[PDB]
Image (tube, rainbow, N blue to C red; front, side, top):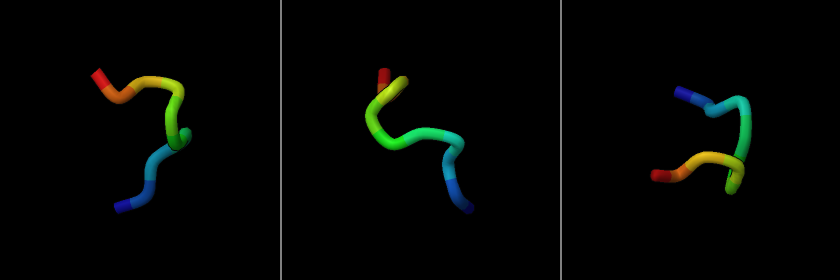
Length: 11
């Protein structure tokens, strides 16, 4: 369950 980014789109 990884994400393409880290703090690029968190809401």
